[PDB]
Amino acid sequence: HHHMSEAKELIKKMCDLQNSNEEIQKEMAGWSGVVQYKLDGYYFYVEYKSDGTCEFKEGVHSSPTFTVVAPPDFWLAVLKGQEDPVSGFMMGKYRIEGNIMEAQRLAGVIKKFQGK
Amino acid sequence: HHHMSEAKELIKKMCDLQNSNEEIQKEMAGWSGVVQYKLDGYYFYVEYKSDGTCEFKEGVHSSPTFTVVAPPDFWLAVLKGQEDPVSGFMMGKYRIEGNIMEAQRLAGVIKKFQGK
Image 1 (tube, each protein chain N blue to C red):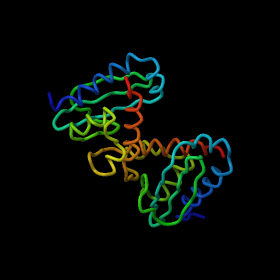
Image 2: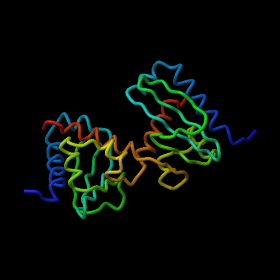
Image 3: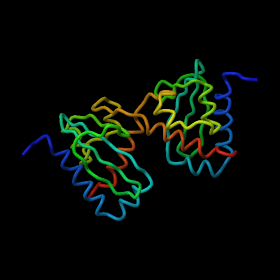
C-alpha cells in the first residue's frame, strides 16, 4: 500500500527510537536545534535537545535551524538507506533552506585558534 | 594601519598554525572540504584534508563545500573573536552560499538508525 505520509511516519518512529535508546542519545547530545520538514504538503518538525532527546511536532516552526523541502517518496527512500542525501542534494533531488550549520561550523573552527 | 586584506592574511596565518600544530590537526581530522572566501574582491579558499591538514589557495574553487561572502572588516573582527559569526549571520552581517553541511548532518543522523 503506497501512501505519501510514510516518510513522516518513519521520522516519527525514529524520534520514538531515539528517545528510547541510551546510545543514540549519547551520540546526539551536545546540540540543540530544529529541523523543519516539508514533504509535499506535510509540515512537521523535530526539535533536538542538548541532552540528546528530541520531539516530533506537527506543523511549522517559526524559526528553524534548517528546513528540508523534498518529495515524500524520495525522502522515504533516503530514510531507508536506499538513496544518498548528500549526492541527492548535489543532483537537485530536494532542497534545503538555512545556513546556520555552515555558520556554526565556522565558529567552531575559529574557536581552536583562540589564544594562539 | 587599516587595510582591507588583513582578514585574508590572518586566515593564511591560521592555515600555517593549523599545519604546524599536532593537536589542532587531530581535532580537524576526519573531514574534507573547501571553504571559499569572498571578502570585498579578495577571492581565496582553504582546502581541508581528512588528515586534519589544510591548504590556503588564491582565487576561486569551481565547487566548494560552501562560500563566505563578507565585508573584510567584519570578518577580521570575527577572526579575532570580537564578533560572533552565528549571531552575525542571523542578523544579516554576511552571507553564506551552500547547504552541503546541512545535507551531511542529515546523512549522519540517518546513519544511527541504520539497522534498527
